[PDB]
Image (cartoon, rainbow over all chains, first blue to last red; front, side, top):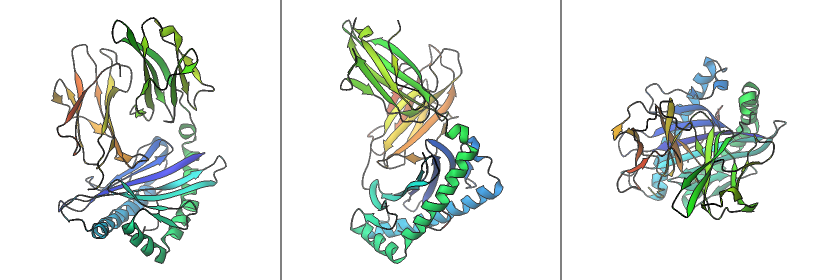
Length: 275
Length: 101
Length: 10
């Protein structure tokens, strides 16, 4: 089961030129494409090795789409200012996210298409891909325009068709990088706080995909209450890292085990501090 | 306008740090809104010029994330840090690189 | 590949 997503950001300037448009494409937790309107020569560019099979005609075509969407977002930003009666002085943000989820047979599971204005939910295509949920009275104006323009039907055509067919093509071309599960490299470190307590930090490094569970156990019992978890973070090589830390009494370390659940591990892996 | 979200900052190496061993210093900035942000890697207080960043992207709560990264060689003597300025910060926040985190 | 059809304005 896999997903493709496109994330767009448009950021208006207060008479500092037209809005900047940035797009990223993701298959699962791998970025494969990008477009930046502020680049010297704005063009879709590759970000994963498996999209580089695609020839010159693919980058030229997708560049047309982002350039049109940049113009579309610019118009959308002008209208949004009016809906909310905001000054032309302020900088504003329109974000979009759309894409498809497929199963192992490559059949559509779920379609997505939603927008955010200044960090708030604005409008979202419903699960049925025929209707829209508006978050407020400005979004209802958009809803009404789009119901008149039969917009959902065009979005549904892309989500159930094109989206699925592209994701299937990428899953055949990047099969061993996209259906891989890199297991995490795991280790525990020990940092004395004081005379009485020490920190035990459980590391997970170089794993893909990002989804992971680190859990500290004392004599097989969960201590998630006393566990500090960092947010899962990119290593910068398309793999992720995470750590879990628990403050334990000095001399009780051998009673603590770290439990790592990850797709790349056949079953959950159990770690202890190794002095 | 509207909503503002204060950025979370993580400073770390791609690989476990080894003195004299070539590595990558990362500054991961996430959970912020709006997208405008200033990020620098510092070596002994000095801005590193040769730093690359990821393309702007966002999470489930629509908050933004970026990775700023640079090739580096750790030493016992050298200090590295990440400097972040955003509308939500009164002054820039500096997070010192700790090998243990 | 992203949506070929122009998306309507908000």
